[PDB]
Image (cartoon, rainbow over all chains, first blue to last red; front, top):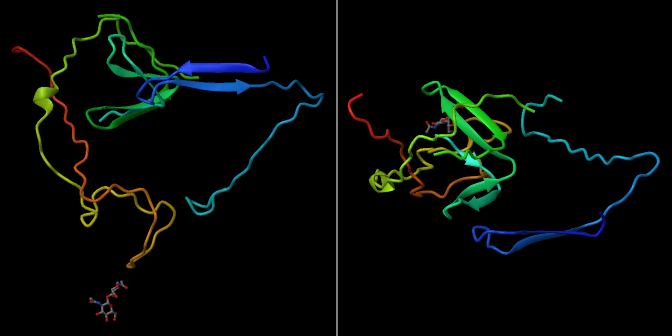
Length: 49
Length: 49
Length: 77
Ligand SMILES: *[C@@H]1O[C@H](CO)[C@@H](O[C@@H]2O[C@H](CO)[C@@H](O)[C@H](O)[C@H]2NC(C)=O)[C@H](O)[C@H]1NC(C)=O
């Protein structure tokens, strides 16, 4: 559900304590939409795409 | 050698550190020095002697 | 999304903790002038020329995390 709080106790190897989060929710649009991110890599490898 | 890599770290049942958590990877050599079996799956500790 | 077997009944072979024997030394630090384990430029190559490069390296002369493996106890065969 919306407004949910997440919390997990952590170990001293990462410093102990808790990792926490808060989350919210959004319902549908009629036409369900998607987000795309596109990133090319220039000279890292064989230029083959 | 064999290397196992992850993000979560936990301690064992007796208290010594060593468990890990969620998706993780390990590589395994075999074939007397030819076979590199590599994966990033999930472990499942066995509860025997 | 994979497939793979499982080995035996849940009864692990008896592993010990005897690092005291394993804590011996064979000191071998690294040397970049000996080119001791350095990544090559992953993107392109050059020839007969000297170039600066920003990359992932170890510090020169480190003593590292040397380990070693060994067999277990045995009696005869
Ligand atoms: C690689 O670079 C070296 C350094 O310049 C080249 O060696 C020199 O080449 C010139 C060419 O006339 C000579 O006059 C110099 O005496 C050379 N230097 C030494 C120390 O001998 C070398 O020729 C280059 N290699 C290639 C294949 O081009």
